[PDB]
Image (tube, rainbow over all chains, first blue to last red; front, side, top):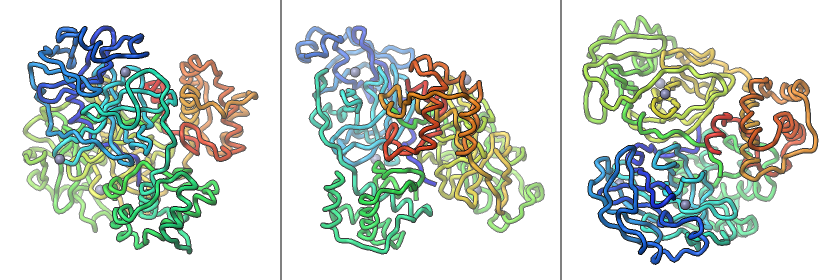
Amino acid sequence: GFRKMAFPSGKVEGCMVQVTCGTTTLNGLWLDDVVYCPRHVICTSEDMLNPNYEDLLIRKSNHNFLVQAGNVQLRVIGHSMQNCVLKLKVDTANPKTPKYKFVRIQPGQTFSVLACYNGSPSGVYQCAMRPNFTIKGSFLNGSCGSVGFNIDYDCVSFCYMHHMELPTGVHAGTDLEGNFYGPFVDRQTAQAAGTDTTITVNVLAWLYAAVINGDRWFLNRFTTTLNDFNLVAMKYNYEPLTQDHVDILGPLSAQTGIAVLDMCASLKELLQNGMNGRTILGSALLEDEFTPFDVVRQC
Amino acid sequence: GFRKMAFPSGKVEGCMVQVTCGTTTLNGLWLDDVVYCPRHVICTSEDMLNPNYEDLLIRKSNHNFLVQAGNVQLRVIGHSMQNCVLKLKVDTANPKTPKYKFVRIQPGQTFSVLACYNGSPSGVYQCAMRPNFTIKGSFLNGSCGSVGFNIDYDCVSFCYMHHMELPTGVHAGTDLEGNFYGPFVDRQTAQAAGTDTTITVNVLAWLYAAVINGDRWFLNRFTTTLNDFNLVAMKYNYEPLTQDHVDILGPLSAQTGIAVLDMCASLKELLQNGMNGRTILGSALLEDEFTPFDVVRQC
Ligand SMILES: [Zn+2]
Ligand SMILES: [Zn+2]
Ligand SMILES: [Zn+2]
Ligand SMILES: [Zn+2]
């Protein structure tokens, strides 16, 4: 069978802490002797309208930051602002610190989010960095500081920290060095996401998953070319397909005996004719939040 | 926002072990001094055509069972068959054993699956016990023994262990005492799932989630009665709605200001008119794998 699957979240659960500074409380990421959290923990609600973060951070010293792991306080002994994240140096290294790296991921790639509330993990789900650098997530109040990650079996690649819901109801945040994905700033003002487009190479990987799992009704007797496939992609706001994308689809092509362009042709007719009320892998729409790697691990 | 969300899987990752007995290797659940796994670990491929499990298990002693946690062997010192599960008593209690209970869940309830391969957690996803007591999962070879669970913040309720893919491609397994959900037996023969029906109370909870999250186009100016709502339910293979279901939807009703029957009326027109190509919460079909409790925790 085939489902949207997150990585196991244990190695990250042991890294989540609660951070308070004033009445504002959000989640933090404790790795070695550093806790990472979004800087707007130092902001009141009024502050968020137009924050001068350097100035706000000057009125704050170490003892203003309340870092808690379960029922234990960690003594802050140094604070820094790296872009939009606060680095709270503390006295004790996290004993549960896995091997980890910080990676900025690319639009179209997927990661797992450990959704947290006041330092407590509440749930885990898989999601994708939309092309317009937003994510469609699930972030209640106090979920700020929740991190996105991938696990390549030994170490945790941290790639996301949640900072904001935007007026569209969609989600924005940073890498773990504090740089926003996309044009967003951690301020409570109007901010456009811009047009979001379907992750074409992912959609194709899904169809390949479908074929592997027995759903192959959408298979056609036509074929197509890449440029003419892309002429329909632009029409239906799909990312243009490249030869790289064709190569990544290679192993799925080599398993299904279905050439990439032949799949591009069936995708073409689904886009120009719709899906007629039928489903692929139990979805009535074209699914773009599985990378070719995601599909491969499930097959 | 709103996504299908699994529980944090750390407390379960530390319980997964690998079990071998012959060339057959699957996953096990190590809690206190007991490892639990599906009994057909004692079966060859030939055995599975018509296994006499008591007889097969007699030819097996303790030293035939290879129980491994990462790179450590656990000495088996007693073996039992409880229904369709093997209870491998071992010498060392699992140090990471959380507080846990074994619960048999009810059709329509949801749980998280920690999908594993040879004792290693590979991913986690949320799913529902379909009314016909199957689950639509993601189970590669060697995923047998993977467990389903809920976490009620302190203890892990284990409710599922995967035993079988059926000829439909759908999934069947047992509670942790070894009793199949549904009419299925751990034998490689033809086995019908029977007609699967939509989990009506869940679908309604989803619409309530949708309303809360801003999608409310499906709201109508009609209303309806419960029996006439159910007269359309039977037509579209939906579980009949009861007063209990209405009560569970209560808090969502009290939050949305939308009476349950008014929602049942909008559901009625979606079932008899379809969804016209639009989406609710980004789905082009009616979603039934969120309980009212699932929706409530996300709101
Ligand atoms: Zn925030
Ligand atoms: Zn690594
Ligand atoms: Zn098996
Ligand atoms: Zn409990």
